[PDB]
Image (tube, rainbow, N blue to C red; front, side, top):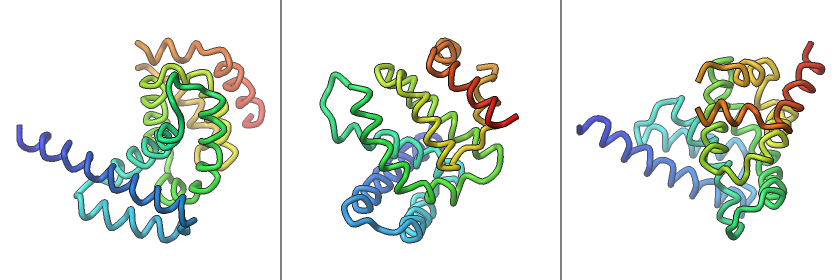
Length: 174
């Protein structure tokens, strides 16, 4: 109906504007503070929730490198492009991602991205390490997420490099 329809339309335009902001941010090296002012204004302009800001920021940054590479999608090439972006914009992530529930919202967006880009799955352990080392995500929420109830998501959690990382991550934490 009209409510879900108009809202899905809003989120789409909003996400397009978050892309435009980050394209400009990457070209200009716009400060994290000014990026946050832009995303905040768009969140009100497009009437999106604060949780939808976090999910959309996560998708847009994770999708950003795809503009920069051909297909078949090659994962080491992906990681090499992604990591400078996470370093640059980690403060933008930390402006919104603050409480345990927020950390799980972002993890679930990261899950959805990997599940939608099966050929990048291999690099998922290295990407979670970057979110962890950059203090975007807490080790304890990463563990919580890994251990959750909800097909393809259960099949992702039998990724080898990931299990290895989940065990490593249990060492630095406890």
